Amino acid sequence: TNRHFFVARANAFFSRLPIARVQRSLAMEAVREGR
Amino acid sequence: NLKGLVYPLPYYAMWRGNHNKYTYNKSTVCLWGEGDTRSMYH
Amino acid sequence: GIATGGRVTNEDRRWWLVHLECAPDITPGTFIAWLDCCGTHTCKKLIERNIWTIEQVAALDSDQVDELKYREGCLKMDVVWEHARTIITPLRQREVT
Amino acid sequence: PKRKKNPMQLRRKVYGLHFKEKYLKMEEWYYCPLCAEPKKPGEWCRREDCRQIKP
Amino acid sequence: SPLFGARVPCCVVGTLRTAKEIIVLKRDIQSLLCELMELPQGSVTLGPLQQLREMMLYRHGTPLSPRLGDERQLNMDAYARRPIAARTMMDVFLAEDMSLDEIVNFGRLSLGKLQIALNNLRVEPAQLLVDRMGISYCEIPSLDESD
Amino acid sequence: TPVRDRKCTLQYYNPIRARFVYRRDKPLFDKYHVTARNLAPGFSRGALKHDWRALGVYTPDHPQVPYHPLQTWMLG
Amino acid sequence: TTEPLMADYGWTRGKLPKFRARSPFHRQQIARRMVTEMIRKDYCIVGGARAPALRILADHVVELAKAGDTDSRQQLAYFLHDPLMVDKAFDEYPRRFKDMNAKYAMMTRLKSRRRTDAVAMYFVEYKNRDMSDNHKGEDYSAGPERFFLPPRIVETEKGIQRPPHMQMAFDRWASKFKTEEFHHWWRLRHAKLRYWGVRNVPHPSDVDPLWTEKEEEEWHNEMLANT
Amino acid sequence: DSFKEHYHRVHLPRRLALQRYARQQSLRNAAKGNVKAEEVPYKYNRWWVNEEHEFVHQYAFVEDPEVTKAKRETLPPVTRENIWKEPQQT
Amino acid sequence: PFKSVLRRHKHHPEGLPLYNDMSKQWLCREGERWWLLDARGEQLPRVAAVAAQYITGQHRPDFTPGMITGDHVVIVNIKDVVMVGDQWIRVPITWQTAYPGGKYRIRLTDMYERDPCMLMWWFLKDEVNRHFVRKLKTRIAPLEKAWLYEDSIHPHADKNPRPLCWTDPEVKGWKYRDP
Amino acid sequence: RCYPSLMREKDRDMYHCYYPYLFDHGDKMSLYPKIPENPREWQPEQLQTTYDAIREDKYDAFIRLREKFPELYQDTRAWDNPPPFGEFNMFYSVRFGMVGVKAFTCKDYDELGNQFDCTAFWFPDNQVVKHSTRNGEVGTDKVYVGAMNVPVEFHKPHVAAFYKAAGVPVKHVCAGFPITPDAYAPVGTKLDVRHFKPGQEVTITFQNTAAAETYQGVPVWRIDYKNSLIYLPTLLDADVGTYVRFSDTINTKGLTLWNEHRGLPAFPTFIPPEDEDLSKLATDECQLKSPPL
Amino acid sequence: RFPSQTMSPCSHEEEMRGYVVSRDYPLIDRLHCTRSIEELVAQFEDRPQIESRVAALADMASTVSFRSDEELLRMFTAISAPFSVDGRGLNFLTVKVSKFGRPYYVPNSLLPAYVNLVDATTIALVREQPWRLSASPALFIQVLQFMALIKVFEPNKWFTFSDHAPSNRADYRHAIGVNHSTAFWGTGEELYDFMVELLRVEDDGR
RNA sequence: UAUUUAAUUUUUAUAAUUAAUAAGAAAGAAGAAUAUAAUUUA
RNA sequence: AAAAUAAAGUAUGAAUUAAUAUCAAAAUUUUAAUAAAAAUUAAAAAAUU
Ligand SMILES: [Zn+2]
């Protein structure tokens, strides 16, 4: 399937969200409740 | 065999075999008391 | 911490302070190579400036830092610098008792 | 092949886009402002003007 | 546990030039900034230079993203933003004795003087920062939420 | 017939010249590095006949350059 | 594999591209002689998926040169067919590249292709050469006269001197092309290629020598003209 | 080209034209100054019992275009706090 | 060749032409007149026959096979069309799809459920194909001159369709004979 | 089982009605068949009923018994009091989803020790770009949601044109949602993430690693409405960065997604309260989470 | 209250003025144009390029209801320029797609631009302001003539590049999805039926 | 090799009113290739 | 089933095969033995793998 919604990808914009920050944030929330 | 808008009601179309694909008739086949038998006496 | 972009947020600080107690034996006189984002190249240029120490990297005037990361070129320097800035005080505290 | 193909079967292959893209296709070009040779954009020459600024 | 050596900035000052010209010009900035806030010498503490990014695509609002003159609150009905004002940032820290109100007051006075400094570009410390020494931009940071 | 020569497509949209707009060329250039080389500010994907600048295209967070009318020699 | 020499040749984006060869051993051999040649002579005209490989590998060699470590010296020494070029690699590149951290090698795609096959030609260089000791002013637009002569120097740069230990080696290497047994090898090569037959290879009686003494006494002349 | 897709090839544009002829009704019920959405009567018999004796229900849903025209035109009010701050129980 | 290999197709986006709007050597619309056929009570097949012959152009004295000149027939009230006796329940409509499982055997009643119009279209198809099969343009072109409306509401007031007054001479009911 | 009960149209008549059968004279509804005003068109053997003590007494009893016992008969109130338009009709309402991006992968625990593999999706900018009702036919309406704001020079010159005509800021990507007329929201509406309740089940359409795939059951785990993420307990076969089209799974085997027991959605669009400002708000206090599975 | 960041200056020519954001911004960011009809006609004529044509139309189709009668007359006059009665009305064709056996013809962005103009006009003159066509015959005739100039009732010749091979792009749809985008666009439907029914008073009463 | 199926004809802003069980300017590498749409770089 | 090798490629350029009309797709029965032979209904676009 060759359409535009499917082919186009958002990789280039990934700096707009802090992936590494949220992972560590939920690490904090992991140790806060003690899993 | 459903495409387009499908309503959250659990099975509406299931008795005509699961589809919406004609629906533009006002006229169907009829026993007595069915639709186009409006105009006949019984 | 390690992978943060741009500015270092305060939450990120919390991370470092959490991992302070993660490693039981640490002293402000510890070698540079225990820091986040201190590579081979980043350690070496600090050494020729006569800096072996977490205290010593916490003693930087920030115009030593930038020419460390611009004129010289140890990248991610402000990360390790700031990493010192945070952690040097708690370390002294844990050193006393 | 089970049979001789007539001129029509031989001519059927040229209607295809694969054939046209491969064989009869004109290339787009301009004049290299440094070398004055015909040039396709994106392909340069071994000349010390054309390596740094590659026109 | 109380929050350690994090410092809340006063202003963040931008420059269109890259980071390598400005290291020469750092000491001449503080001498100007001190008389912007009318504080004595050594009062302001400038942070490390930050060269942000050379963005081909320009992702907006990003940690390294070059700032632009136009602002949404500043011009609402403009359908786009004015192009890039600042490629490098350096932070402005005051003494730690200034509480949150004071810091923001010295932050506001600065935008006050600098805006007009850019509009004189249509002797006093403003255009000294603007004209012969480059700084094209300034901002007040957002208070970080993370405590 | 008049000759079969094509007029300039160098300023039109091209899908294989389109990819090189946002691509990173730092190693290709020794002395002369430019901010973004293939990228024409205000024009759709680097093409000069596709000018969008100083039109009504609403782009809240990205810059747009103003309109100056293109010369005759830049198009063809 | 994250180690800045050792090569991963795949097609996935984490891997640098595999250029066609017989075996990964063969790929390694090829890569090694390419890197050796590029370090010896700053440019390589290299076709195919080989050139990006050369780019990345050259960047690795400059990284090792900036390391300036005995382990780095040794690991680069494992990699090259030339020991001497390793010494060249640790004398030249640090001063050359002291102001740059990233992308040390410039790749330039040539608009000409091999006649032999459709594979494209790339021109791979080291970057800034005005900081280099032996490569200071050289012109690569066209080749030298006979390929054992030192290459062209730009007219404004004529009077440049090069590290003595390098032109010693270069002259020792070039001095075996002036003996007549090389001329016999040349004619005999004509015979061989003509037998394997390859077109446009003249008969060995038409093959008049690469090196004569008149040409040497003018070449050395202009060479001390550059000195 | 079977029977049926040729059939629809010809006739679906004709169905469209026919319902266009249906839409002009409202149009001269517009032009002469009347403004009315032609109403559909409510049906009180939607609840029934079939031959196997169980409960059968018919669903009649009536679309109001004067509501729709208001629905698209302006925002809804603020989402009530009982909705997002408490989860949906599984 | 004369007729090309590259041919207009159903999957091809150019689409399939409508012969009413087409202008071609063998299509003459100049001398046509519009008819109105009320199908109330008349048997489906008969109506199909009459409509087929007005549509085809066979009702004219000057009718020529290769020259397609029809009259537009507006067939009104398809819903009231009468099929005699058990036939609604017993008369098959069979087609074969090319794929594993080549049989659809479908009662008139089911086709009438889906569309009543498709029944009249089906029998028109049959009565036109009875004399024209071997060429596609001669099969398809007439059929578009039928306007099938399943009740008394039609767009065509502007053509002033003349009521087509026809009584079926055949006394007996229609008889399904198909091998 | 997977069929509902079969009732024929012939079988719905006065003797089958659960409630009293009502005849329609058009200005008035009565329980007697309309007596035609022209008496000579009365058919033979037909009783024109002006009064019936049999069918009127049951109606008499029924109505009173309704007003007299309103607490028992509240379901009966469905007969006399139909729901008006909008107001989230449970069976008739279909709202739109929004366009996400597969951001990364993560791991969580529930209350118990259980390892989950979450996939984290990102909702960069979701705005209602377009309304399309096709020729005014009922049940044909679409709402087009765009995502990921993109510089002016990106799209082919015909795409940008579309966005200029719409008035909406230029988006990377647009997807249509078929929806009912009541579920509309105006053009340019910023969509938030808590449009999706953490308890619900979501239909997902994305590109496989290389055709399109649809997952019709997948429950929401967790929502970051600061960074506009949403977490899901699945491992997709999908490239990171793939645009993923979201919808509500509208029925699970005879059960409606939204009902009084299960819950109710914020219907046409979610809207945030005027008093909250996300620029003052941290990540951890911004968290929403499902009930335990 | 006050700027969060500094604003770099620009002179009078290069500001982005001419538009306004919607009343409720944080919820709806739609952009509505305030541009006068003079400068939109000016933008249409002075910069003849395709994108400025589309850019003119997207503004003057946003603002149809918000202007008077004569202001519309100059609009349709300006817009009717590149149209010849003899020539095909709406065909703007850019790409020849030879992908299939017989070459496909793809239009450019101008087509849906003009069509969107006609549909905006439909919303203005029929639904929300039904009185306007009856009040002044001037724009009745102007709209009618513009609507005859582009040929709205044979869209098939919008897509036809050679009159020997008439293209069915508009009248054809297949169920596997060909021509969902070029499908039956009711374009002049509501308008023409309405402005026929303005003349449909056959009643002798009035 | 013929039929037959399956895939493709190289980003289609969009998908399904029916059949059966869908297509906007173009080719080198889709990567300037060592997973950042430039990590400052002469 | 990971690893190594080989397939769009520029150049050279054979061999088996060849009664054929631009082709022969689907189904049903019949005809002196598969029946691409009939008749009828039907519904097979082009290129490449
Ligand atoms: Zn050149």
Image (cartoon, coloured by chain):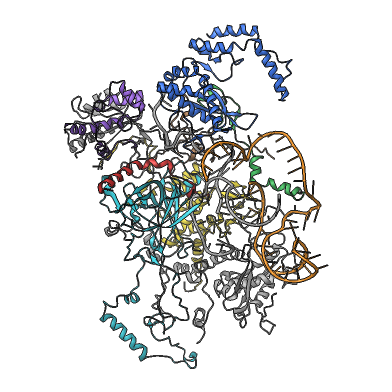
Chain colours: A red, C purple, D green, F brown, G blue, J cyan, K yellow, M orange
Compared to residue J4, the image places residue G26 above or below, namely above
Name the spot of residue G110 as percent of width and height, x first: 57, 28
Name the spot of residue J51 as percent of width and height, x first: 37, 91
In the drawing, does residue J231 fall left or right of residue G104?
left
Number of numbered discs: 0
Given residues F27 and G14, the one toward you in this image is G14
Classify residue G215 by image quadrant: top right
Given residues H90 and G85, the one toward you in this image is G85
Compared to residue C37, the image places residue I80 above or below, namely below
Which residue is pictured at 49% across the width and 15% down the height?
A: G134
Compared to residue J49, the image places residue J189 above or below, namely above
Compared to residue F37, the image places residue J212 above or below, namely below
Which residue is pictured at 32% across the width and 77% down the height?
A: J76
In the drawing, does residue C81 fall left or right of residue F32?
left
Q: State the quadrant of the N terminus of chain H.
A: bottom right
Residue I73 in view here? no
Name the spot of residue K96 as percent of width and height, x first: 60, 46
Residue G190 in view here? yes
In the drawing, does residue G139 fall left or right of residue C29?
right
Query: Dividing the image into four equal quarters, which quarter contains ligand 1?
Result: top right
Given residues I56 and B18, the one toward you in this image is B18
Classify residue H89 by image quadrant: bottom left
Q: State the quadrant of the C terminus of chain H.
A: bottom left
In the drawing, does residue H13 fall left or right of residue K20?
right
Name the spot of residue A24 as percent of width and height, x first: 31, 42
Given residues D32 and D16, the one toward you in this image is D16
Q: Residue furthest bottom?
A: J45
